Length: 275
Length: 9
Length: 98
Image (cartoon, rainbow over all chains, first blue to last red; front, side, top):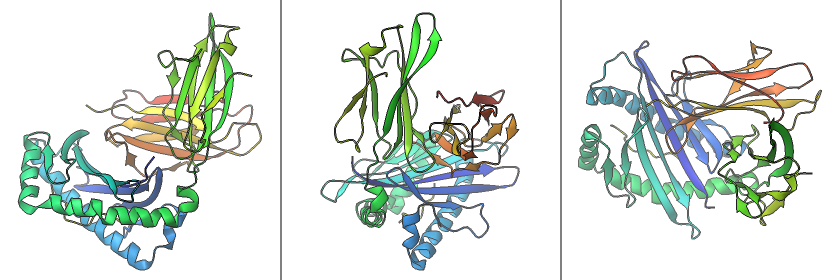
């Protein structure tokens, strides 16, 4: 329901090359709008949505500076993390951070977050109150004390309540013709052979935005998600999304099943069945 | 706009 | 603790022969991020674009590999994925029903 601005950072160690790679991407809701890649020659923050291109040179210059500095600290940090976990230099390891703000209906911060992971495991996270940290193990406790001594939480809280929300608001207006116009799914049902005593009915939702959607199968109003195949919502490639839900039903019994679609761009729930 | 401040594990 | 990739192969629009389309291979839920995702035409690697590395709320990564294609009645398409969690490459064929 509420809009969000989020950034996703990935740093990976490369032992063979004796260096690391840092990749940052930025999103408004389900729409990517910037990237940074330390591996790119002369790396800069680059536009990845058309509406962000109207930002001036000061924006691209200053965003690029931020990422270059962040890239270096995440590279050095990979070295620390290997020492914390008694790891050799032979293996590759992965450090991630994500952070963002959700826009409340009053224009205030609904919820902000800042979290970190190492080799796919929660490492440290800013608590809901935006004033303290939770560390996952004895290694993360080293980081927590460093950040407490340096008062890092106050800066993260200031960013999340302030610049994050005001940036979100500026971006939503700049790209309002796409970011604030919900595209409803194009829906249909198909039938396919399955096995003895059973044909498959597949309910398609195609070309919708934003990503959140509800696809359910009902047999006389009763939810069938137990025997249902529900695929992960997937990108269309043009900024919209797709999803389907499929169910095996008895032959001749097709018309006793209904597919129900809920989407923000529909404004009224839909029912449909096999034709 | 990205968060600026020094980020050191 | 490494997580294996899930793979979907699909067209941007419902396929009709002789009409230009887009072919997508969406690979998600994997960790670590090192991966190789090839879209294949009759077994041969296509020079398809790859999205910027991103990840989900559970820290697992996702990538979209995609390219233009005009489906017909003969050409066969698939997606081939190699990841440290797979002892053999994972291959998913494209059909118009999924």
